[PDB]
Length: 95
DNA sequence: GTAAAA
Image (cartoon, rainbow, N blue to C red; front, side, top):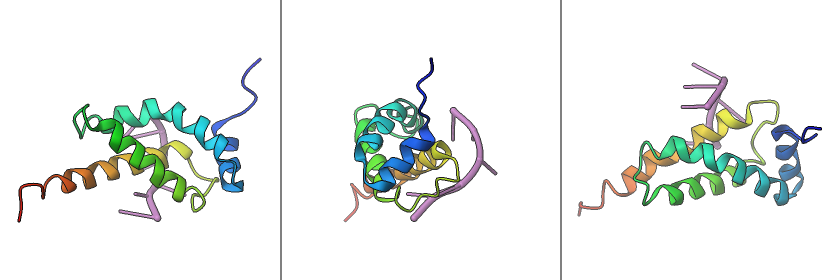
């Protein structure tokens, strides 16, 4: 019974260099992190903002403290990546 | 870089 594995152990594996655990950890939260940022960007660009937030989560996962919440730190990165995309198209009409 | 919980 159960999956025997939790999101906590998925995060420690990617700190050891096992990106295979991050791959299974991304697709899991890819549904939740996308529901957050779809509220700030249109559904035509939302999968591109979600993937940028995951590449930022990988390069910062070796700086993440496993002794803290994995999801609260994941959701904060995708919505902060969402504001920066709105600045990346907010200057789209400027010169 | 991102740290309440979603």
